[PDB]
Length: 447
Length: 85
Ligand SMILES: Nc1nc2c(ncn2[C@@H]2O[C@H](COP(=O)(O)OP(=O)(O)O)[C@@H](O)[C@H]2O)c(=O)[nH]1
Image 1 (cartoon, rainbow over the protein chains, first blue to last red):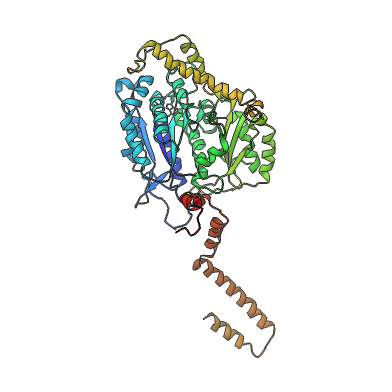
Image 2 (cartoon, rainbow over the protein chains, first blue to last red; image 1 turned 90 degrees about the horizontal axis):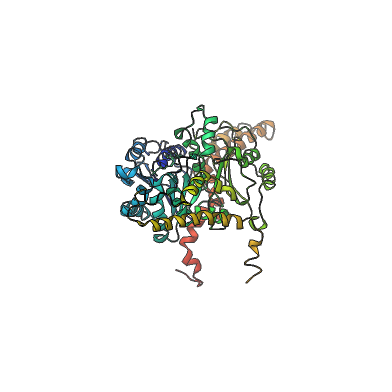
C-alpha cells in the first residue's frame, strides 16, 4: 500500500535541481550538510524523518535513498561538494566519454544500454536494501539527452524487472524555441518512452518558473540557479503526505489511486502558492488555494485554451479550516471543466508544516500546491513540437547524430522516429477522447 | 508529605471548625492536587501520549501503521480459518 522510495538524478539538470531539493529536505528534517541530525534528541514526534527517503545510521546521519547520474562528472562532484558528508558518493556515477557527452542523443542512448550494468548496479543494490519498497523518483529534462536515454532504458528495464513498483519523474524542459532543434530527437524519444509508463511523470517547460523567479526573488536576472528554487518548492511539497502522513495519503500508491484513473494520461501540470524554499501570502486558507488555479502562477506556459481537466489534486499546508476551504472548493468547481466522464471527485489533502522549519510567526500563512491532469498540458513542450515537426516530417538528420549502431540503417532510424511521433499524436488522441462523455458508454452500454 | 501539610493546615483550623478558612484551604488543596496529578499523568504515565496513540491506532489516526499491518497481515487476514497461530 506504500513503501520506500529511491530518488534518481539523471543528467546535470537533476543535480542542479537536486542540490536545491536536498538542501530543502535537509532543512525540513534537521539533517544538515553532513547529513546528521541538527536537533537535540528529545525522542518526540514519530515523523522526525522519513523512512522512505533516508537511511538513518548510528550518527543519526540520514543517507539519502538516492542515486546520482550525470554525463558531466563536475556537476556530480559539485553537488557532492555541497552535500559535504550528506550525499554518499558510492551511489553516484558518470555516464561519460567527453566526446559523446556533447551529443545529447548519443550520450544518453548509448549509455542506456552500454552502461546498463553500472546504471543498474546502483539501482539494484539500493532497491534490495529493503523489503517494503514502493518506487523510484527521477529528476530529469527531456532536453537532457543524457537523462532521456538512460531514463528511457530504465523505464523499460524497471517495468520488466519490477512489474508492480512505481516509477516516476519530474522533468524540466528549457523554455526555448530554437535550442530545441538539436533536441528534436532526444525529447521526442523521452516522450516515446514516458508515454509507456503510467507512473512516469510531472512535466514542465520552466517557462513560467523562469518568469516567477525573476519577480519573486530579488533578482531579475532569471537563470536556472535562481529558478531551481521554485522547482524545489513544488517537488518538495509533493511528498509532504509521505513525510508527514495522516489518513488518505502516505504513499504514491494512494496518490495514484485518486489522481490518474486513466493510466494513459499520467502527465501532470504543477502550480504553487508562495513558499519559503529560498512567502507569507497574507490570506485565508481558501484564498491561497484558489490562486493555484490562476495560470499566471502556473509553472509552465501559462494561459491554456480553456483546458479540460481529467483530474485535479491539491495539498494545503498550515492552519487549514475545512469550512474556509469549502468556499474554495465551490469556487474551483465552477472553474474546473470536464465531461461527465471526468467528473471525478477532486482530491485535496492537508499536509503538515515541518516542525524543523523556523517557527511560523503566523500559522494562518497557509501555503499549498496543485497538480492537474489537463488536455492542454501538451502545449508545455510546444517548442519541441515546433522543431520536431520541421525535422521528423522531412527525415532530417538520420544518423547524423552518430547513432550507436542502433538503427544504423536510415530507414530503421526513421522507423524509431516514426514511433516517437506516433506517441506524440496518440497522446493527444487520448487527451481528446478524454474530453468525451461517450467515453463512458463504450464499455457500459456496449458489451 | 502533601497530606501532612494539609493535615496540619486543617488541624490548625479545628478551632474554626467548618468555616471560611477551612474552605480556603480546600480550594487550594484541590488545585494543588489536580495540578500535581496532571503532571504525573503525563510525565510518568504518558497520559497524553496514550491518548494520542489511541487515536492513532484504534481511531486509525495514522495510516502508515494500518497499511503496514494489513500488508504484513495479508495472509493472516486472507486465511479464512479461525485459530490462526
Ligand atoms: N531546470 C533546469 N533545467 C536544466 C538544468 N540543466 C539543464 N537543464 C535543461 O535540461 C535540458 C538539457 O538536459 P541536460 O540535463 O543538460 O543534458 P543531459 O546531461 O544529457 O541529461 C535543457 O532543456 C536544459 O535547459 C538545471 O539545472 N535546471
